[PDB]
Length: 245
Ligand SMILES: CCC(C)(C)[C@H](N)C(=O)O
Ligand SMILES: [Cl-]
Ligand code: NA
Ligand code: NA
Image (cartoon, rainbow, N blue to C red; front, side, top):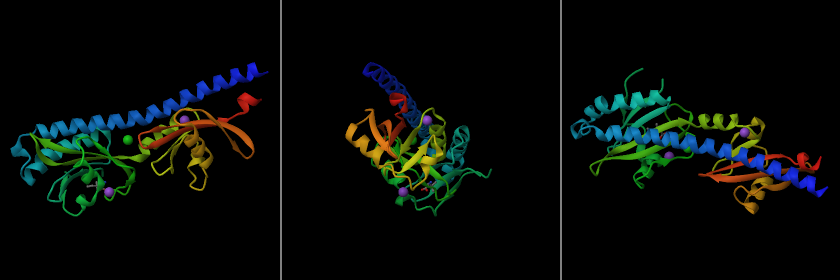
């Protein structure tokens, strides 16, 4: 009876919409927590007197402890300050104090370049950190003291941390990165690189953010929706058995 099928469709749409929104929130809260942390660290570095910032030895001794404590507070992988001479003061997970490194090619990096092109925090796509060889998301920020550039702050957070948060959420939810490659999922099988996601991705392009759609898998009907969340695409799908059976 159409009345009953409509009531089941409306219910499951609501439920699945809610669950999609939980995954969206997870991504938003991960980002904003890292941004706030990065902003706080900027403020504490820029608060230092100029004298503490204008020789490399003073940067080591005065900025280094701040990087280390901040790193520990959030269990970041790397926290660092890159200078215009190409050196970077690096606090890395491993208890030796932070050291100035001249070998990390920092002006070639997008976290460095892009921080100098915006007054905001820059957020990288996930990429393989050169130092610890883990996949990270980097938050970077050009630090200025009274208009004068001190250097570019960077904070590397393992991308696994966001993957793990997403996976824990309820519902059959998943994320794609900017390249429409699968990035995270509640059901770990979706992460197989050989899975074709065109049906979902195509139905999302046709329907738009948060607009619920029908599609087929192995001749069976499924329901889903996606929405953009920053550069990511977040999706949920389920079997259409709830409305058909
Ligand atoms: C100093 C910059 C490092 C920490 C090496 C950054 N993850 C990068 O890979 O560029
Ligand atoms: Cl993020
Ligand atoms: Na780069
Ligand atoms: Na989920």
